Image (cartoon, rainbow, N blue to C red):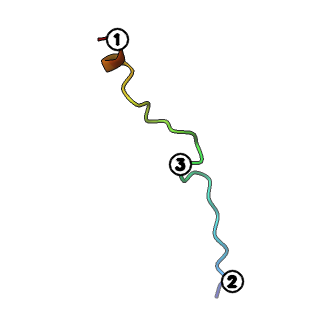
Amino acid sequence: GSKDNIKHVPGGGSVQIVYKPVDLSKVT
């Protein structure tokens, strides 16, 4: 019913490290 089932990746971490490493600890 479907072609080759082509994969699409709108987002797979491609977005850019959204999770910021904690910078607050850095302040000390």
- How packed mark 3 is, by other alpha carbons closer than 10 Å (few <14, some 14-19, many 20 or more), is few
Q: Quadrant of residue 26?
A: top left
**Kind of residue at badge 1:** Val
- Circle 3 residue: 13
Mark 2, Cα crowd under 10 Å, few <14 / some 14-19 / many 20+, is few
Q: Nearer the viewer, residue 21 or 2?
A: 21
Residue at 44%, 30% in the rendered image:
20
Location of the N terminus by quadrant is bottom right
When asked about the image quadrant of residue 19, the answer is top left
SS for callout 3: loop
Query: Residue 4 bears which disc, if any?
Result: 2
Q: Amino acid at mark 3?
A: Gly
Q: Position of residue 7 (x, y in %)?
A: 63, 70
Q: Residue at x 59, y 48 (%)?
A: 14
20 vs 6, nearest the viewer:
20
Q: How far is mark 2 from mark 3, CA to CA?
A: 24 Å
**Residue at the disc numbered 1:** 27
The mark nearer the N terminus, 2 or 1, is 2
Residue placed at 49% from the left, 36% from the top? 18
Tag of residue 7: none
Mark 2: amino acid: Asp
